[PDB]
Amino acid sequence: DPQRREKIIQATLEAVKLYGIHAVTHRKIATLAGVPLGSMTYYFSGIDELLLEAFSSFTEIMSRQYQAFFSDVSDAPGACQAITDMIYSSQVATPDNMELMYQLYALASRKPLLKTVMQNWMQRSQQTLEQWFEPGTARALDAFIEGMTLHFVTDRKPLSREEILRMVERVAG
Amino acid sequence: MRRANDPQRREKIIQATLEAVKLYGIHAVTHRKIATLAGVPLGSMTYYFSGIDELLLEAFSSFTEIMSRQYQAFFSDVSDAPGACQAITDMIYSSQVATPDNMELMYQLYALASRKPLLKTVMQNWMQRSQQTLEQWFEPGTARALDAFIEGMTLHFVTDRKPLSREEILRMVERVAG
């Protein structure tokens, strides 16, 4: 029962990866969840609220990962090393994470509820960084993470770890 | 020699492909959907582009070529590093890059690229062009840091409930520039 609701949230993310958000429906999700169609009506209302809750679950997973990179951080230089680790490890920009994250980004202009999820997600990230950095620098760093996590796993010749550290430290001021 | 490669059908098909991605989502686009949008016979589809991935390749390559011309255009009046930082700030603060239309296409490309090597190639080529633009005024390492910063901050600027000011952005760009 809470089992089932969670299966449906997960199948929603699975449907986004398999079908694209545009093509996601209650029945496609129920199929992937292996639950009766009736369960969709029981736990959820509209496809957009379901998308909201599924992507919120996803970003919460991401936030826990994000924070975990700073578990051994006690100061700004340490946070720079942690951000470097976050980028260089390629653990944030995995195929699964990218496929979900960028579909969210793709449709946020068309779906206000999803833009809210992105904004909330950015806000949590900033809040993590504000433990060691000024608000503005925190935002700069999180945008730098956004771009460099992706570019690191895409570039035919990405930056070295020591190069990444130097650039993180530049942004950190 | 079965194939004829008509350039008219091609450009039509390429535009219909981009239209299909926005209508249906990149995951759901098929030859059938594209040909219907193009107004070309479904049969013609495989004789310009083998399959769905190579068609997507061509269409997104067309898209990023447009993006790159826009990108380079921000540097028309740049002759030094401070001017370049201004141009980058312009690019971010103008919100002209991260438009709804642009974001919808670009992030769908990004989303599917780990699953589709040809699409990753499009991203890789696009990054390389951006870097070569920046490398006129910045060392390669710094150029990559700046382009990644542009990637992230163009999105964050149009998304954040409370985004950075222009002076803040310029300051950070100048930090990255070193």
Image (cartoon, coloured by chain):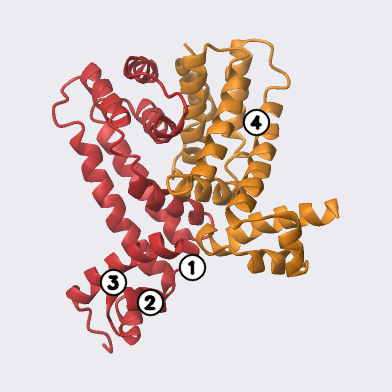
Chain colours: A orange, B red
Amino acid under label 3?
A: Ile
| Dot 1: element | helix
- Check disc 3: other Cα within 10 Å, few if <14, some if 14-19, many if 20+: many
List the residue tagged with mark 4. A66
State the residue at coordinates (38%, 77%).
B50
| Subunit ID for the residue under disc 3 | B
State the CA–CA distance, disc 4 to disc 1: 31 Å
Q: Position of residue B53 (x, y in %)?
A: 43, 67
- For residue B28, the mark is 1
The residue to which callout 2 is attached is B50
Q: Residue under circle 3?
A: B13
Q: Is residue A168 left or right of residue B8?
A: right
Asked whether B165 or A143 is in front, the reply is B165
How far is disc 2 from disc 1 in space, using C-alphas? 18 Å
Do the dots labelled 4 and 1 sit on one chain?
A: no
Q: Quadrant of residue A157?
A: top left
Q: Chain of mark 2?
A: B
